Image (cartoon, coloured by chain):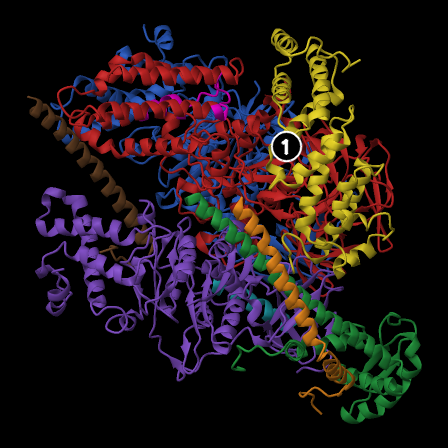
Chain colours: A cyan, B yellow, C purple, D blue, E red, F brown, G orange, H green
Amino acid sequence: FYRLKKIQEKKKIIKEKSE
Amino acid sequence: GIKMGGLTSEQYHSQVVGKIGYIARCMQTIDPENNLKKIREDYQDVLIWAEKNYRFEEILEASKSGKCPNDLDALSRRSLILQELLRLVSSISPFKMKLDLIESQYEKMKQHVNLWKSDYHVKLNQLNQLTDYLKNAAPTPKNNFLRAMTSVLQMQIAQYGITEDNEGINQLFKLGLHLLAMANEKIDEQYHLFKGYVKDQPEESPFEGILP
Amino acid sequence: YLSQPRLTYKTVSGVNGPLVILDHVKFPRYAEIVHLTLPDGTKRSGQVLEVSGSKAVVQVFEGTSGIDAKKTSCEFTGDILRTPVSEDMLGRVFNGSGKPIDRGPVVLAEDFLDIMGQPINPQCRIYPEEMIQTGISAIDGMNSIARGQKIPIFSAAGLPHNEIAAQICRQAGLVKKENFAIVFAAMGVNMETARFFKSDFEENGSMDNVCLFLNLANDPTIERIITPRLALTTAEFLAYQCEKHVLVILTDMSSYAEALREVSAAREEVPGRRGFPGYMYTDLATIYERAGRVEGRNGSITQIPILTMPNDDITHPIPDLTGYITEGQIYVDRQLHNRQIYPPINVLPSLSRLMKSAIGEGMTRKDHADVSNQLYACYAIGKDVQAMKAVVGEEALTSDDLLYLEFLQKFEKNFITQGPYENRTVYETLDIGWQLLRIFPKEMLKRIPQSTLSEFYPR
Amino acid sequence: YLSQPRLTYKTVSGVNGPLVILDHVKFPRYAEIVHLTLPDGTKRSGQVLEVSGSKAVVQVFEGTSGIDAKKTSCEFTGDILRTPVSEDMLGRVFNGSGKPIDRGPVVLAEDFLDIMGQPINPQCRIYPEEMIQTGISAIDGMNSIARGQKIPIFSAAGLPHNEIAAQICRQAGLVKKENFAIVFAAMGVNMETARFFKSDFEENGSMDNVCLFLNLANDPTIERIITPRLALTTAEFLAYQCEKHVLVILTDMSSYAEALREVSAAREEVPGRRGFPGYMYTDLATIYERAGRVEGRNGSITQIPILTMPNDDITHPIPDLTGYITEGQIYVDRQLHNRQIYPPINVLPSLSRLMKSAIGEGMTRKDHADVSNQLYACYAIGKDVQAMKAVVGEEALTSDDLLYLEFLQKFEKNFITQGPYENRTVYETLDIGWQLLRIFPKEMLKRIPQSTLSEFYPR
Amino acid sequence: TFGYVHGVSGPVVTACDMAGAAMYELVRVGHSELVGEIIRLEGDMATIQVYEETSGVSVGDPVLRTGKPLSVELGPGIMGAIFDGIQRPLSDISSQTQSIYIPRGVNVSALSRDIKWEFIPSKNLRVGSHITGGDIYGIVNENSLIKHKIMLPPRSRGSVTYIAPPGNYDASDVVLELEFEGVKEKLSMVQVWPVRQVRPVTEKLPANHPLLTGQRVLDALFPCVQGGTTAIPGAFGCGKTVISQSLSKYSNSDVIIYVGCGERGNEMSEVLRDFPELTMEVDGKVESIMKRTALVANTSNMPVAAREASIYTGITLSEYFRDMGYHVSMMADSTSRWAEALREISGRLAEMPADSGYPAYLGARLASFYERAGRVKCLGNPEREGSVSIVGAVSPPGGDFSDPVTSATLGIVQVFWGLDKKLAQRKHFPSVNWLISYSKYMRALDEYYDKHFTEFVPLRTKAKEILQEEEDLAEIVQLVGKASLAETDKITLEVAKLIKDDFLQQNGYTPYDRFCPFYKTVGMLSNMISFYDMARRAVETTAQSDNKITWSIIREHMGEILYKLSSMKFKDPVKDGEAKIKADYAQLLEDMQNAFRSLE
Amino acid sequence: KDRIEIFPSRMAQTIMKARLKGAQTGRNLLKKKSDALTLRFRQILKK
Amino acid sequence: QAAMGSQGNLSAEVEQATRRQVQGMQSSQQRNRERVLTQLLGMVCDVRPQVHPNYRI
Amino acid sequence: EKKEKQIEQQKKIQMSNLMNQARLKVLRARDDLITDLLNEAKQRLSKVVKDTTRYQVLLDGLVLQGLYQLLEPRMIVRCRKQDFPLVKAAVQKAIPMYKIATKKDVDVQIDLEAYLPEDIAGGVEIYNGDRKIKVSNTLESRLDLIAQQMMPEVRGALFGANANRKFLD
């Protein structure tokens, strides 16, 4: 669970940077 | 977060202003003619703040600054004693109590270690149970018996008080409460219970001059 | 001192759980304290746990319920939570935030100490070499307490660990044949527990030497992880600046661990076991290691970090990480309590890591260490015999086994059982030890040299 | 009605697995139904799962293969999924989407209902009373289904849970000491079993009172999620608006749970316990609790969810979360199946919490409760005696033990073993019970009052 | 006061133009006014957790901001009503709509504004007087049982500028006006209090007065005290109905609150159906229990926010009456159902799970729940006192005690009324396990018992010793058959049975045993223990040689005494008064001692 | 010693549950054997 | 009864020692009050403006 | 005898209670003494403010000091109306200096619509352009800001040093 949560947060961060 | 007991800083001093105003209101309500001189003196430090318009805020500042007797626990006990005295005279309102007995009962309460848990407190709670019930009661044998018996009970308390234990008053308490809790459907038992009171009462005409 | 005016901000960026994130902050400082006012006038405080550029993350102690985004007003004090300390804090009662709750005034500081503290230079730290007489045979004999030692009581919900701690507060003396200043941090407890200790301290006639910090079950969970630091910070003032011997008792440390775990989850930190932060050990060491004597100064701090073991699991991270940091434990259990044995102290899973130096010639009696070690052997074997006999039956036992059952039965009722007000000396405890050891023939007392048996055993 | 022309968009921002991300969509709704047209003229359905400003994200029911980002058009309906309901749809067979697959016409609606519906106001919920007999003795004379309860059938994979479910549909009805309907929904069913249900229901004349929904294993996984909602949406219409009693059977809720996990992954939600969503609890309650009696109306809904236990472990979140919010369990075993007993239902681990109200004079027969309790004790004892016999032998048994063995053997052969096409009413089931009970003399039937024995025991 | 919906990702709605919003504020999202709360905030955007289904919500929909966080509406009309976990009257929703469903976005005021309540001022206050928080300025006459006292809301004070005269007012009128520092506040009869906030009291007092339930077991051996906290297991076969009815019907508390957290629909119906049919004698009249009861109903398919909030809504209602000087007894039907709702929300928020999947703060939430119970000194000048008791039930999956919810609860509650199913199967009620059950208030109540009854305490001590010994002897009896057994042990075994049969067992479906007054409970135990001691002495003082007394001699010799002891439970307090029952029990005590005397 | 020392796994969980059921059945079957022997023992001792 | 009398009179003594301590405290600070006010007021009046140590450029 | 020992225990608890309350009473009296000093300091500061020839100089410092703490391109200076002529001068003499110490051009305006309460002893508060960042540099704020840090020295200066403190660590 911990790793998956950080993966989802990192994906959100990557998406924001691309915008 | 000074959290003095269960209260914060503003709430603590607000409760002190409330209790002081309350005592002033109780004192004028119980003794509007200012006859109870000894009892009033015991409260002079909180009655001196009465009959002034402080709009709450100026007496509130006096509490914060330390000019008022702002100890919360001392006010709690002293306020309880006064309002319990009010209950004593209020619950027997159809009758007048002698001023000497009011002061005597006051002194006995003031000396009590823990008035709230006293037999004095319980006896008043039972009396109010019996006198509140009758406030909105239909005509019926049970309620006529309770009303007649309550008027005698109030008459006796006005003369003996509550702290001065008296077998006559205690027996009447038991009979009144036992009737009150008695089933409304049962008529013969409440009739025999009332008749027992009437014949056992030391006098011959227990209600003559007590009720209309 | 800090002479420059502090700045006030209305620049809150957003709120996420217990963390209020501000932007547009001038030169944010890490681990500085921020005071914030809610639109309704409520005042709350928090600490900056992260800074980045113009942003800062503030953890609010009271909580984030009702925190606005447009009307919230925050000011930065410009320093870390340094707290006022004075000698006359003894006899005062404080809350978990450091404020008085006894209707007395605020602290009139002699100085301001950093709640985070400083580690004591190991070169100046002086090894503890003095024994405290707890009066409890289960402790003074087999798990002695040194002055400056860290000994929590491992307990479980419903057991009388509060009574044992209270007892220790009154009948804790020295074996040099003394008034300890007690700092009691009541955190994560109900009113009745906090009132129990407060009443006992007054009943003992020692309240003028007791400083209380209360943080009850209905108080904020974030303040519950500074209360221990507030208690210990005061202890450090008293012990290391005023040379007063201080006894610091921290109530169920598990409420500290749970408060910490909540913060760890809120900040998405790397878990270790059972969801607790991977740095739980380091954080506990920050609390626990504020103890011991310092060379050249006549003060000391002794700790008793009592903790409740979740589900009696001795391997739970809380007792586990504590066990790694503290000098052993007293440890009570339900097997003794369920038989109305008090104190219900189980010596077998217990230890005192300083006992080897606080006992013996010049300290108590020269046979102390020998009696303890043999009692441990006999007690453990008696438990082993019961484990066997439960299956094989009494008829399967020989005389060598029945002796340990006799020892075990007499040991628990004579040595461990005492009562809340039974205060035994260390010398009486050892004499009792011998009375139990004399159940066995000399040849079976294999942990004791003949140079000791020949002198003490015959009596 | 809306009477608003629909907008069709050709602006597509991207496509990611089952999801199509659209752009420039005007005031999109969440859960809005849209229709796609692919370049090949192929039409597909989908539902909007996220609307972040003008960026609508739609999950396509069918596969997304063939969809581009230049020509594919998306027609918005302006509304959510609302199912056309009528009385006439009873006797029809539909797929998961609500479309007919029986060569009949599309349903001519009497109304449109939101398939998610609303919770039933507890103030108007009526405690379950009368019984709905199933025709299967193992669950009529032992753990009957009250007219309003929700009692699941737990089975391991490979057991005949589908054959029993079909038998219940053919045989179930009112006690009859015209107003009864069955709504049957199969989620994730394979082609061979789906045919079984359809053909078995049609051939035996039961279809007139059955509304059948088939969601096949190779059908869209999102359609599997609405399937049970469409079945209950119909059940609510039929039951509460048309004053009749509806039995709803939800087959293979475990396959539903797997489809739910797939939807959660589509939303990029972090999986919870054993991979399932953290909201699995409320989702099952949302489906299950849309049942029971209501004040002032003569209709009712009952449910018999049927669940495959992964690895035959009742602890698994699927049967655990189900049972935690249902009233008892039927429980189909494996030992009875391998012994070639049909139905293979084990009466000892089963329970119907409402049986106490379901049965008795005025609902079934006076002696119902007494026969059940005595049969249960006799079977439990017979199993206990059988275990003894295996150790001590036949010659070590007394006469009473032999009677329990005779009961055990004839109980399973006569009472539990039935066959798929023998319909045993509640009164025949009780009569069979008495035939087994008359094995014992009156004095051994300790759980049946003497008044009951004198009335029913002889003859 | 409006913002707009920016987007929907499921049950989570993102709002824009919502800068002026506080965390855990309330919003009504969309044209159906869906109930939800604001959790995360960023800039002028807010993340809204919507309790109900979000299907149909559009981008651009309005969001109405409500200044108050999740709160309970408190005022006249609260009594007799059934509420949702977030304070929605179910009896009005079902009656104002003629529907059977709770409408999506239903917006029915917690307290109706069409009732003209009978309000009487205190008659002690005057315009210009000082009033503080918790003060009572008038009473509403709701029914014959509970007077609904109107208090000044906490965190308010000032000078009184208007007092409404006695008359008929509804909940939308103005009854009292007060001015503090030039700011005038207009108050009606209804106050609003955030449900997660603890209502202040003057002081929290020790609990010393017993909770006088009607059962002999769960009183004599395992006392509960007004203001105390207990736990009761909730299993199908445990017979929990006995406690619920006995506690709600005959308790010496004033107000009963029954809180559902998220149970099976049919279970919620059983409670809602049973409660309205319960009655009790009061002043000789039989009154419906619903005149002094309030109930919160939540089924497993209710919005998770309500199922989680239900437990706090209940206790907030409890404290409201606590502040009136009433003794309130609240039962949470299943705290396990609440814990399940809490875990669901933590899951939805993607929080890191802890022990057995529950939130890390599970224990903190339970601890702060139970800490709110207790006997208190109320706010306000009337110097009144009251209490809240909690008798919440636990029902962990599987019946195990390892679940963090039951383990945490047992570490918090001071009394555990452990029930069993085996006893129910044996038809022995109330189904009390005895060996598992405990009470930690025995010391707190020693002052009461010593003051009023004196002999009760040694009797309950001996009673537990007899029952425990009966269990301890079980292995000896199994291997012996009472043959190679001491006569003193036979007394323990047979007397312990007498206790189990004709004292701890109670038949609540009989008119004479509906409620056992304490004086009768201690009377029954006193005679049984006095018999025990006499039998022990009769054997022990004669057991030397030549001429000894045995149980066979005692049992045969004075069988009428054993019968009279068993008959004691039939002394109906409704027909046989306190003096008559005590007199008959005194006669048995004398007859009993003389029966043994004839043997020496 | 204290544990069978099988590495944590879903496979181990399944095995332990089957092993526990076996142990519980053996306990009950041997207890019944003992009870049968005890009655006869008490039967034969009575004889 | 003797104890209540003896215990009641003890507070008078506690009170007498307390009153002396308070008056002694007031007398002592009267010798420094003026010096402290001068020192404190000077610190208030002396503004000492400064630019944050980390200001760049 | 046991009850008497408890009666003696009751007597000791009453004595313990009495000594604890006496301690709190004298501590409260000590805090009143500290408050009287601080309230006198407020009156002394007011007397200083009344002196134009020192108050204008104080304002010169107070305005410039706040400017260095905000380091914003736009400033709003808020004061009580009575002192406006001197705040105006304080700003005029502060800007030439600010542009030298920070090498940044700042637009400093005085708010002529919003004023500080008339009961403020003196001083100014400065807001940034959007009024989201403010520095409070009035006399009451300064007195508490310093007094709270100097208190350890006041404690000793008025009541004496603690004879039991030997180390300053």
Q: Which residue appears at 76% of the width and 87% of the height?
A: G49
- Residue E159 is situated, as x and y percent measured from the top left of the image, at 84, 48
Residue at image mark 1? B120
Q: Which residue is at the front of the view, C304 or E409?
A: C304
What subunit carries mark 1? Answer: B
Q: Which residue appears at 34% of the width and 72% of the height?
A: C130
Q: Residue farthest to the bottom?
A: H100
Q: Is residue C216 visible?
A: no
- Residue C403 is situated, as x and y percent measured from the top left of the image, at 13, 51
Q: Is residue E429 visible?
A: yes
Does the stretch in magenta take in C22?
no
Q: Which residue appears at 84% of the width and 45% of the height?
A: E129
Does the stretch in magenta take in E497?
yes
Which quadrant of the structure image shows residue B144? top right
Tell me how many marks there are: 1
What amino acid type should be assigned to the residue bearing mark 1? Tyr
Q: Which residue is at the front of the view, A16 or B109?
A: B109
- Residue H76 is situated, as x and y percent measured from the top left of the image, at 85, 78
- Residue E492 is situated, as x and y percent measured from the top left of the image, at 28, 27
Which quadrant of the structure image shows residue E256? top right
In this rendering, the answer to whether F2 lies above or below E556 is below
Q: Which residue is at the front of the view, E285 or C178?
A: C178
- Specify few, some or many for label 1: CA neighbours under 10 Å numbering under 14, 14-19, or 20 or more: many
| Magenta-drawn segment | E496-519
In this rendering, the answer to whether A18 lies above or below E540 is below
Is residue B12 shown left or right of residue E164?
Answer: left
Q: Secondary structure at mark 1?
A: helix
